[PDB]
Amino acid sequence: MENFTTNLNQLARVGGIDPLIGREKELERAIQVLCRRRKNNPLLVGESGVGKTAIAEGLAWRIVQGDVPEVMADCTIYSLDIGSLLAGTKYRGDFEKRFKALLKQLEQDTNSILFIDEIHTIIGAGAASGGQVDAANLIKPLLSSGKIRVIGSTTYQEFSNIFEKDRALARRFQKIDITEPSIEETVQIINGLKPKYEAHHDVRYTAKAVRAAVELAVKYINDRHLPDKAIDVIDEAGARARLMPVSKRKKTVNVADIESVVARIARIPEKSVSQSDRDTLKNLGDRLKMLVFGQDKAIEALTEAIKMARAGLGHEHKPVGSFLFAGPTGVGKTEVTVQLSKALGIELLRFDMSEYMERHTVSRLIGAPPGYVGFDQGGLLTDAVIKHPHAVLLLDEIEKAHPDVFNILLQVMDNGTLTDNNGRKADFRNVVLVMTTNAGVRETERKSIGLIHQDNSTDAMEEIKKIFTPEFRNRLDNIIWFDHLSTDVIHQVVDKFIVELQVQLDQKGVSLEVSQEARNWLAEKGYDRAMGARPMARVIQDNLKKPLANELLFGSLVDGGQVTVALDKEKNELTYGF
Amino acid sequence: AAVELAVKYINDRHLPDKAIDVIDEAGARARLMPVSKRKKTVNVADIESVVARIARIPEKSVSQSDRDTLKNLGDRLKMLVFGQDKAIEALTEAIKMARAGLGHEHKPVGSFLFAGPTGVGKTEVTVQLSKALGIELLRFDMSEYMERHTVSRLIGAPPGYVGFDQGGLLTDAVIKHPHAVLLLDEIEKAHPDVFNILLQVMDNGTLTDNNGRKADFRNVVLVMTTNAGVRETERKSIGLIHQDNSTDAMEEIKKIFTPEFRNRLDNIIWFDHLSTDVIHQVVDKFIVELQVQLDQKGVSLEVSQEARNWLAEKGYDRAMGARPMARVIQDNLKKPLANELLFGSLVDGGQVTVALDKEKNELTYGF
Amino acid sequence: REKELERAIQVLCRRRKNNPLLVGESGVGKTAIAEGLAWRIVQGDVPEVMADCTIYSLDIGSLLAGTKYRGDFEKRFKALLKQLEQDTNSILFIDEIHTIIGAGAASGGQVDAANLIKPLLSSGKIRVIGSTTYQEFSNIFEKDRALARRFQKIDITEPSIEETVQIINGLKPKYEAHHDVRYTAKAVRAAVELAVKYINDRHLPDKAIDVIDEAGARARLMPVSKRKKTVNVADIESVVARIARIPEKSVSQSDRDTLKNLGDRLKMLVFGQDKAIEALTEAIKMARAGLGHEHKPVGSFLFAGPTGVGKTEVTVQLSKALGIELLRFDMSEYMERHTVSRLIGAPPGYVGFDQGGLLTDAVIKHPHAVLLLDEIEKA
Ligand SMILES: Nc1ncnc2c1ncn2[C@@H]1O[C@H](COP(=O)(O)OP(=O)(O)OP(=O)(O)O)[C@@H](O)[C@H]1O
Ligand SMILES: Nc1ncnc2c1ncn2[C@@H]1O[C@H](COP(=O)(O)OP(=O)(O)OP(=O)(O)O)[C@@H](O)[C@H]1O
Ligand SMILES: Nc1ncnc2c1ncn2[C@@H]1O[C@H](COP(=O)(O)OP(=O)(O)OP(=O)(O)O)[C@@H](O)[C@H]1O
Ligand SMILES: Nc1ncnc2c1ncn2[C@@H]1O[C@H](COP(=O)(O)OP(=O)(O)OP(=O)(O)O)[C@@H](O)[C@H]1O
Ligand SMILES: Nc1ncnc2c1ncn2[C@@H]1O[C@H](COP(=O)(O)OP(=O)(O)O)[C@@H](O)[C@H]1O
């Protein structure tokens, strides 16, 4: 007792314990257990960081304050330091000697309570070249006789996995569940605790700041539990605003600072648009339309979803956007998404649904069940989302995956959460789910038989409905049906590819100019409505790169200069030179 | 009473210690009661309260505030889920029979299978029921359980395997919250082999995880939501007259769920589609939620009545239930609102009025 | 890393659980970030709150060395804890935070360095900086809820191109002193860009610097005839090629000749069907001339025609003439849908998982090769 436990009453007398607020029924039942005749040993079990240790030390704090029923008055709770207890037990019997001496001291006191934090650790305290003769059994007979009182604290998992193993020790304690408090209890706890943090960080918290901290930590941080994550938000806000007086920012911590802390912790695009975040969102449709020609309404839908997200009008809990892009090949379905990722400056999560042809490939997405060979790997999808919570999720050619795999995205779109094999949950509320497919293509490109050609516009939707279950479609933000590229779009695509080729050549230090009629001839040569834009890339490659490759590989353009490409009219041929 | 209740509701210790602990805690409680000198005998009510607090289960509460909570539960839910009253009625009656003590022997509070077209309040009624009771909500998306060997994920890996020390998720959750609402979403999309776990649970209210530990489901409401049988109900027959395909819905459900599984259910509540007035109420609900979102930004909003009617007429889709209304309201309101909140008039200001003209059926905006 | 360093400093000055956790992919610079915080403290490039603070890198080996005689490890650990508590101005840096969840005494196996430290961290008594990769974190560290709760998660993200360029600029003098070689700015930028484009198995601030160091080391092995030189873009290209398997600038050698006479060297082996040799040579030339695709295979060709016309022979001869391996797959063996699992592997939890995929592994082992799909109509 001299130097192995710390007097918690002494701490509360010197203010070393943060004050216990609320927890009325919990502490009342802890006292009730303490007042039993036999096995008066309460065990505080609960989630990690919900106030179990807080309750245990707040009992002694209340004793010092005297706001306790007049049966635990003058009782002194001591926190056991197992670490220092085991320090010098090098020789046989030292541990048992010191432990039993402390035990008889506690027996003689008849007023003290021994609080053992993380009591699940005492299932072994030294069997070094020996048997079960450690503290796990030394403490057993004293509890059953009701001579001493011990308070335990452990999480549900550690309890179930370690403490429940020894039924003899397990039955000597009274399990008490410390549940996570609700909103009002948490904000009141913060109200009672924040004087100390204001003192430590030399700041002031507004009431709205505290309420916002509570609500945001609730709806944005799903890693931890309320009474600790809220005060963590508070502490980090205090520290940040305390580091600001380098420019003499002696002021209160308003709501905006709380949102800064929450966004920097949860890695979310918060803190209201502002600065230029507004400029970037404003001309995003432009920066995309200059790289994706035609199919502008897809860019419109994407930008509207992103803005609604940043404007605070997003969904309560859903991905930023859940889009199904369907249309013929080579019309920019994946390109608009990749360019959106590059424009926003965030991560692109590309997944090739063609690799998920079989039903049993779901385990590749979410991980293998426990006990199996691939358990230690987790799942690819959820791991990627957890690593990059703010990103764009691209699922290429979802019609190629097994029709059953869609049921994962079902829950992902509905709730924005996905649980891997470890019970961990990925947060999809900050991702844009975009799925590309060629579903309605073959049905729209059909030939009517009869004297009257029919309207086949609805056939793309018919095919998509036949492929995707009604509940899967019912969770999509919108289905943007892409149309084929028109000839002016083809000219613009040819120009974009010319710019790409020019960049490639500038890398080699040579310049290229292509006459306008040459561009027109290339467009008229390569245009194929049924195949979109890839034939343009092919024809441009064949017509320009191959002659250019020969010219620069074999001397004529080695460290060359200007490439002179123009079109003649008699043969529709191109010119070349240095 | 101490003996009987410690037997029936404590299953972690052995009888000669269970009863002694019940009696000792009752004595300590009656000894702490006389802070106002109420040194009394231990009545049956005190023993019942002690065991209920030990078993973490609800006691007799026909007088407390939760009696009123149960009194107005059906209405406090009907204000959030419009139509489909029979589901709310069944849920509330099951919760009452459990709380009234006139419950099932050792079964869960209620075992209900919710089936019907998508986009209706099958899962939403469950979320709002968990909120209205203030009890934990355990959500399990059975779509993550397509393979038959994912049962190991539910109940844990057998001893002598890599995933043993983690334990099952379902049993661990129920251990953490013995009084909760258990939501199993899209169970027909899980592997049909998984249904046998639910067989065992529904019949006995107990479940043994990998550690031989038994989870107690007697105080957990079991609600499972499916979209099974919907294809037939909405499938058009060929002929001059269409048939009620509800018989086909029943046939499909029986195809998917073995006879004993259907026998271990409290009821199968067939959710209906949403009517037009129900659509109007849904529009009102979503507009209220949008108004809350805007007030978070400091923007008041007023939407006219005929604008509401026009939104409902534009978004009404019988096949998809209430979900299309979300998109309709989204595009028709949030888009101009997002523009005005980002690079427009509604930056730190509100008073946005939306009204419908009759020449173009368009919306008004602005300060 | 001023943003991340500022986040770390903000975390350290907190009242409770003021223990930042540097989480990031390997090679990103987590250990580098901690030791550079120490370095800037030495140079005073810190806010006054962290000034005059001493960071200690905790060694686990020497801490557990010889800790027989139950209590030796505990006594030693508590002695370290007491020295740090008395210092009141020290931060303990644990390079591998996921490795302190076990400290022997498997009998019972509970009183380890993890449970020994939780009271200190929860009380805000001591400041410790951790570091771990993402998978180690999520599979080893975060499993201990109470320990993960006492640490503040900081994501150390992969830097950008220009950030990498500046990092290499700042690190260059040490590599110069080590190799006695000098780097040109164009060479550094080329190293960064080529490492991004062609090296796929590492992350920027550890693979661009890898190219820099290896170029310096090889140019240090050039003065066997005393070829004293600075590192130009050419050496960088050679280095990045030794991993990408195709040099871009070495084409100024006889590689130009091999390209030029390739069509003929094939025509002497494949008679007729000149169109195929022409197409293949044009594709390979466009690739080697830098005009090829930046994210596509060198060439994707479907050869169709009657039997015995040289469809398979021309590809084998092309592989021979180029000196590259022939990744040969017969699509008649993949006549069934489920056979794709041979090419890509089985999902986790299934019998063939640890084997991997045939095609992907063959491609990874041979980054530069010709892929032949015999009888594709049979798959
Ligand atoms: N009633 C309370 N009053 C004030 N703070 C509380 C209360 N309950 C919890 N806390 C906060 O939680 C922290 C203490 O956590 P607690 O001891 O409850 O969990 P724990 O013992 O750390 O759990 P584990 O052993 O799983 O880590 C304190 O920093 C405090 O801010
Ligand atoms: N609107 C467009 N503007 C510019 N380039 C385009 C456009 N549409 C297609 N492309 C070209 O096509 C390539 C990408 O095509 P994309 O991935 O969009 O096709 P897709 O719609 O996915 O068809 P599939 O799924 O069948 O491949 C780009 O390299 C780009 O040059
Ligand atoms: N009765 C209702 N009242 C109000 N809103 C409803 C109702 N039914 C559904 N909704 C809307 O639908 C959303 C919840 O959908 P839910 O999860 O119930 O779909 P579901 O029944 O699972 O369909 P599926 O299983 O086919 O996906 C809520 O956001 C809510 O706005
Ligand atoms: N901020 C930085 N400035 C310059 N170089 C850095 C920086 N961060 C990392 N590096 C480079 O990375 C190397 C050190 O690796 P670092 O400590 O960053 O990660 P690590 O210790 O390898 O991580 P782990 O411990 O997980 O393996 C150094 O050689 C250095 O060149
Ligand atoms: N055009 C050709 N020139 C020279 N040899 C040829 C030609 N076509 C076929 N052969 C010979 O016939 C054999 C079969 O050629 P291959 O291309 O593999 O046939 P397939 O097209 O059926 O795969 C080869 O070994 C090759 O030597």
Image: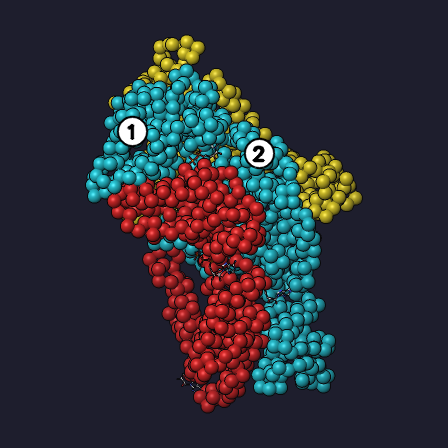
Chain colours: A cyan, B yellow, C red
Q: Amino acid at mark 1?
A: Leu
* Dot 1 crowding, Cα within 10 Å, few <14, some 14–19, many 20+: some
C145 vs C198: above or below: above
Residue at image mark 2: A198
- Kindly identify the residue that appears in the image at 51 percent across and 20 percent down: B65
Mark 1 element type: helix
Give the Cα distance between marks 1 and 2: 40 Å
Whether labels 1 and 2 belong to a single chain: the reply is yes
- Kindly identify the residue that appears in the image at 77 percent across and 45 percent down: B360
* Dot 2 crowding, Cα within 10 Å, few <14, some 14–19, many 20+: some
Q: Is residue C73 left or right of residue A30?
A: left
Residue C138 visible: no
Chain letter, disc 2 residue: A
Q: In which image quadrant can residue A331 be found?
A: bottom right
Chain letter, disc 1 residue: A
Q: Position of residue A574 (x, y in %)?
A: 68, 82
Q: Position of residue A505 (x, y in %)?
A: 62, 76
Report the label total: 2
Q: In which image quadrant can residue A97 be found?
A: top left
Q: Amino acid at mark 2?
A: Glu
Q: Nearer the viewer, residue B356 or A33?
A: A33
The numbered mark at residue B143 is none
Residue at image mark 1: A102
- Kindly identify the residue that appears in the image at 34 percent across and 52 percent down: C62
Quarter of the image for the N terminus of chain C: give it. Answer: bottom right
Q: Residue furthest right?
A: B359
- Kindly identify the residue that appears in the image at 74 percent across and 37 percent down: B351
Q: Is residue A397 left or right of residue C356?
A: right
Q: Is residue A473 left or right of residue C101?
A: right
Q: Nearer the viewer, residue A246 or B10?
A: A246
Q: Position of residue C236 (x, y in %)?
A: 51, 73
Chain-order first, disc 1 or disc 2: 1
